[PDB]
Image (cartoon, grey):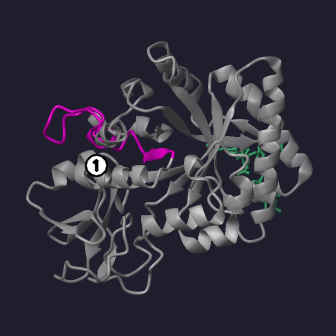
Amino acid sequence: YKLICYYTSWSQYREGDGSCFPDAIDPFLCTHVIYSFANISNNEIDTWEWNDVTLYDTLNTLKNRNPNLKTLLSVGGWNFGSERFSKIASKTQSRRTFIKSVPPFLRTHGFDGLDLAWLYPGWRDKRHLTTLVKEMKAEFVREAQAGTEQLLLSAAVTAGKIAIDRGYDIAQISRHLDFISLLTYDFHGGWRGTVGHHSPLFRGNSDGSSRFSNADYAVSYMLRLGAPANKLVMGIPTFGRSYTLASSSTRVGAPISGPGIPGQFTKEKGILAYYEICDFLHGATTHRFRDQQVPYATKGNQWVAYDDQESVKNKARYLKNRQLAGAMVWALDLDDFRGTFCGQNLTFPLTSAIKDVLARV
Ligand SMILES: *[C@@H]1O[C@H](CO)[C@@H](O[C@@H]2O[C@H](CO)[C@@H](O[C@H]3O[C@H](CO[C@@H]4O[C@H](CO)[C@@H](O[C@@H]5O[C@H](CO)[C@@H](O)[C@H](O)[C@@H]5O)[C@H](O)[C@@H]4O)[C@@H](O)[C@H](O[C@H]4O[C@H](CO)[C@@H](O)[C@H](O)[C@@H]4O)[C@@H]3O)[C@H](O)[C@H]2NC(C)=O)[C@H](O)[C@H]1NC(C)=O
């Protein structure tokens, strides 16, 4: 099985114990580690952070201890303008300059491949995405004639039916990609005025109006569109989403006024790291959506949807039962990476739980 784990460059700036450098990563935990995110300047791949050159180097020394570990560099992301990707991909001269700049950059800094995180192509972009993937893969194939191990190409793909239909020719891009990570953890957010879970495994016979907003539907739909099971990797989150309750109601369908309050270390409205949730749970009431098979917790006017060891092991069993290529984790720096917040002296408890399931029959 593959275990694909993202590390995010901005996690280095978090204070005290929340600070996470590539250094903290156990080299034997994941099969592939992806560094997020690279920039595009002058139509060429480039660094984002001031000290990226150093961090690349720290990440790639993990390979001195585990020579089988693979590392990828992810380009794009949320803070990258979708329109900036659109402009690059739709003009042949810009697209060509970009593609040619990638292999030398990856080689200089020690990466084994490139992850595309264009979030998200519009209906006008779908054709250009296909072209970008095709031509990117062709160039990696050509570069490997120089006797080096061929660069890997992956893509992060949204799990909502409408985003898929609008932006992605799954049947075509599947043939050129080494793996596709399905982002099965954005099924709810502050954008609706109610409480709900962003990563449910199943629909659960109760659910109103969205048979499609669950991991099971997204996986079955990708399989139907022509993504081969052995290229499909199911995304499992290591963070939670928080909401401020608008009333004293805390069950399904409850009102909300907005995001939850920022966490001590992540400092971002609406999300919490798992190591912050471990702390939040002291004094919280815990519940579990039995149909959806995911927990949530509530304390005061704060309502948190999250994943724990049981829910993550369940998702891992599901994906094995479906014979998928593996699991993808967003993100190593949001799991309890020091191992000192969540009880047990177990570093990476969520990621480890996934690995345990994937390593059994
Ligand atoms: C990821 O990469 C991206 C892509 O490169 C990085 O984003 C860019 O990087 C640089 C530097 O930070 C900037 O590049 C040049 O910017 C200037 C361009 O000028 C413009 O400013 C005006 C604001 O008034 C703005 O508005 C319009 O244009 C005209 C203005 O007359 C106006 O009539 C219109 O109505 C518009 O309002 C316009 O959009 C431009 O942004 C240059 O001045 C910069 O410095 C050089 O400039 C001169 C030569 O051109 C020299 O005199 C100077 O000495 C110097 O050499 C610079 O070259 C970009 O702004 C920026 N672009 C994008 C796409 O965002 C990004 O930083 C990176 N991310 C990270 C984390 O690194």
Answer few, some or many: residues within 10 Å of disc 1's Cα (few below 14, many 20 plus, some between 14 and 19): many
- State whether residue 219 appears in this view: yes
Q: Quadrant of residue 190?
A: bottom left
In this view, 26 is above or below 195: above
Q: Is residue 136 left or right of residue 213?
A: right
- The residue furthest top is 64
Q: Secondary structure at mark 1?
A: helix
Towards the viewer: 76 or 206: 206
Q: For this rendering, which residue is in front, 123 or 189?
A: 123
Q: Is residue 243 above or below residue 281?
A: below
Horizontal and vertical percent position of residue 175 = 72, 49
Q: Amino acid at mark 1?
A: Tyr
Q: How many marks?
A: 1
Give the image quarter of residue 38: top right
Q: For residue 273, say whether it is visible.
A: no
Name the quarter where the C terminus is drawn.
Answer: top left
* Residue position for label 1: 274
Q: Is residue 335 magenta?
A: yes
Residue 257, quarter of the rendered image: bottom left
In the rendered image, residue 208, in percent from the top left (x then y), is placed at 37, 86
Residue range corresponding to the magenta coloring: 325-352
